[PDB]
Image (cartoon, rainbow, N blue to C red):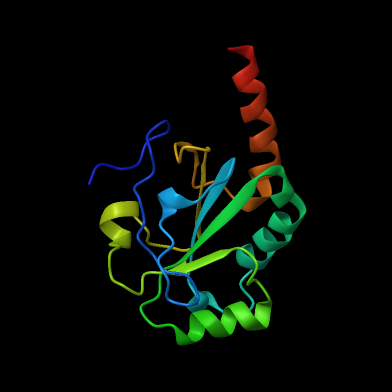
Amino acid sequence: NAPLLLGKKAPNLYMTDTTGTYRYLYDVQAKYTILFFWDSQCGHCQQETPKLYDWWLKNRAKGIQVYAANIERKDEEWLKFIRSKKIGGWLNVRDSKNHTDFKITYDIYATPVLYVLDKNKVIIAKRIGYENLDDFLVQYEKSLKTK
């Protein structure tokens, strides 16, 4: 695996939603997709996940989905976190059908990890913090105009 690059299509993910039903990354329709890899075992009070959710609630009508890719190999703790932290509204998925190698394909070590993708799943931001999203989207859109 070569490391991921700006301007390349993010690798597809064949992950499943909270009902166990396939929701492929490439099948998501959204002006921007936030690809977000996370792990409930990082703690019940982990900060990035619910704060991104709060951000998403405020910005989603702009045409933004979060493909919230939980990296765990069991359902129980993932679902418990979704319920208790009340983050069920976005696209929660897990690799329940074993199609994703998070280390080879996406280089996931420490979690959480965030990518911003455009409408065609091209990588436009790599591993930036949720707190830099608003500014990243402003500058990105200005950059489309200039040229």
